[PDB]
Image (cartoon, rainbow, N blue to C red; front, top):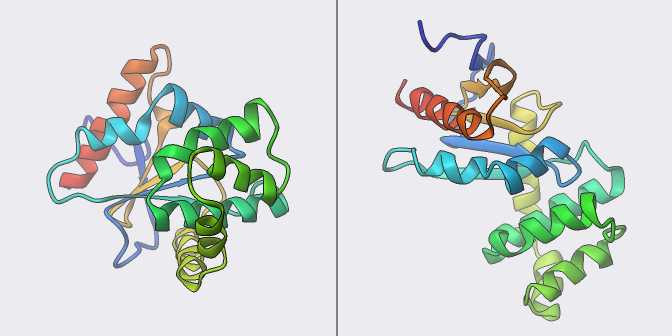
Length: 188
């Protein structure tokens, strides 16, 4: 076939019921994740090819960067609750991996402040039980699917993208193959 299990994607032995349609996992500590966001724009190019009726979800993971890794997961909960993912994603990545100016929770906070979220609003979000449950959601989804590696995308809780089995000579071709694969899986 042109799409085969074990080539552009793998199937879960243990399919996850109720799962989000398109589910993405990342860490701000994850270097391929950086590429995925700033060079490849994977999430975006996937979106542009997904059907209609298809919501995209993206969650942060704990297993990279120890204490800071967890702070980042809580911070991304704050980002999701306030709907400011698109304003903090890049400064968080560059603060962690490029400039190395993110070393603590206060430093993560500064990124939000500089992107224009109010001090009070952030701290109140940070400490809210709505954010607690959003953190629980992130962990539960990663737990539901054996997650020991990022970046990772799952379609309908059954198919996991396998970018290792795609061409990387050309970045644009890699991205279209990836998005087309997601689309294929989504129609399956």
